[PDB]
Image (cartoon, rainbow, N blue to C red; front, top):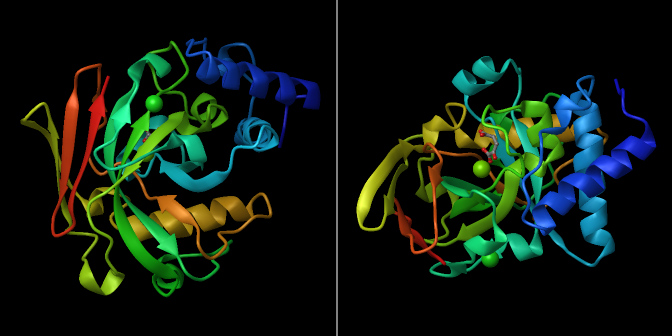
Length: 263
Ligand SMILES: O=C(O)CCC(=O)C(=O)O
Ligand SMILES: [Cl-]
Ligand SMILES: [Mg+2]
């Protein structure tokens, strides 16, 4: 399942994290370790998590990447990917993101869930997830691949924590009974203009499925989704570059809006 030595995992994690911490893009790691499997990549990502926990960061949630059947097929993968969210990733609705701490950030409109019951795989699917949802909450992610490379590389991206870097919760919380996630419309505005549109169904056909896929992915490593877990279910719209001076508002049908100022 794995081709990296443990020393390589540790060194890769340090190297990839350092790119984030030092705001310094690096070559995608699969160029130097072309044999890396997803298990290697997750070993690396999880070691990054450890490095963050070790210096006292709290891990406050999980995020999903590649939550598009089309994109999965394009990238030659059969499942989404996930990454973790550190406490300092969090930005208040309307808050400021300091781009000088970021490399080449993009924002995406997502819907997050907080669970109220444990979920696990393998074999988790939508039906298992429904009963476990406490509420949903509009969330914009700021993603920022630490790689200098143009073309998306799933295994490198995983090693780089699915490009996670900031997330902004906002809008209004709602129970599942109050929202239809498949038809929940989102409008992303940047500097006063509509730049992207999407509906919840853009996430796998049903954003809650993202949670189940997460459960099954975590099961591959003998982990699950504890109750109370905050999960960003995936990009509803295309990701949009942001730069200093940009202001963005993402409007969620019936859920208010999430905004952020970039400096
Ligand atoms: O580009 C993708 O869909 C996966 C990587 C990512 O950063 C994300 O979607 O959160
Ligand atoms: Cl910041
Ligand atoms: Mg995302």
